[PDB]
Length: 380
Length: 7
Ligand SMILES: [Ca+2]
Ligand SMILES: [Ca+2]
Ligand SMILES: [Ca+2]
Ligand SMILES: [Ca+2]
Ligand SMILES: [Ca+2]
Ligand SMILES: [Ca+2]
Ligand SMILES: [Ca+2]
Ligand SMILES: [Cl-]
Ligand SMILES: [Cl-]
Ligand SMILES: [Cl-]
Ligand SMILES: [Cl-]
Ligand SMILES: [Zn+2]
Ligand SMILES: [Zn+2]
Image (tube, rainbow over all chains, first blue to last red; front, side, top):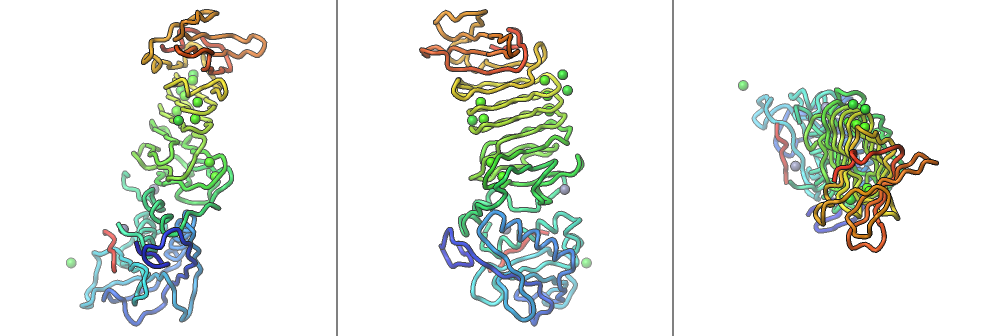
């Protein structure tokens, strides 16, 4: 467990310097044909550095001239024999006090290295190489440009987590306010590959711009299938994301224990708020609002379903079968339990769905619905 | 201590 702070030193921040080498006396690997970073490489390298400082307590300051630096960047083009090397990609040296520690090197004969802003593998390579220079040891043609779930955990173990990042209400995906290219989709042709770090506020996964059937999971540490890819989005350990918006596809939106606002969008969606007081919008289409236990919608913290469509949407209470299939009752409970009732509040046009579970002395489950609902909309 | 990235 090597870091810039030493060996087996955990949770300690670092202030590091970096430098784009303009010349070298030698490359520590023995490769030759040094070429300095071009303008695009410089911009993309800084974006990679930023993606690391976003998640862990690292500060990076550029130095120039003859000043030494913790982390350095340079290209090579030839092997130790002086022959052209068009085959290799990049490498980096771990932190330490030895010559070349923290240095990272990239093959200028690779177009992805020269053009990391338009060839995604180049940006990913920068991020990856920097990870090693910091002490880390280890999708349909696209490459994630920022640290993924395990590396976020690992780098935070070394340097501590950055609790100042995006502490406001943050939106990831379409309509993003992150000012990070890897969290931003500007149109439906853009692929998203990221693991979100977010240190506070009420946040949204906006994947509204895609037509693919998506699976969006708001659980900490969980993976989502977004924009037609699989497992391309995850939520880092230590992060709570609150809201999700699906696209025009037939989606599955899985909430977490927090109070979530879930919007299915068009298409026939499945929405599962989970624990907490959730607000659910199925959107256009034949949507299903799923309840997996009495704890999903207690009276003290009940769900709202804000756009329910009688005769079109469904509410799934089949999970309650495990203690005896629910019986639907018209306007009164018997006291026997395992009963469900739809109660119409004519003054406010709200339907209250009350569910009385066996063994409960009071009716403890409620979902409030803005609109009418029928017995035949309820799956028991 | 050097780590290589795949090409
Ligand atoms: Ca936030
Ligand atoms: Ca949050
Ligand atoms: Ca949808
Ligand atoms: Ca929830
Ligand atoms: Ca829908
Ligand atoms: Ca609907
Ligand atoms: Ca809930
Ligand atoms: Cl050849
Ligand atoms: Cl939950
Ligand atoms: Cl639809
Ligand atoms: Cl509809
Ligand atoms: Zn690696
Ligand atoms: Zn892409």
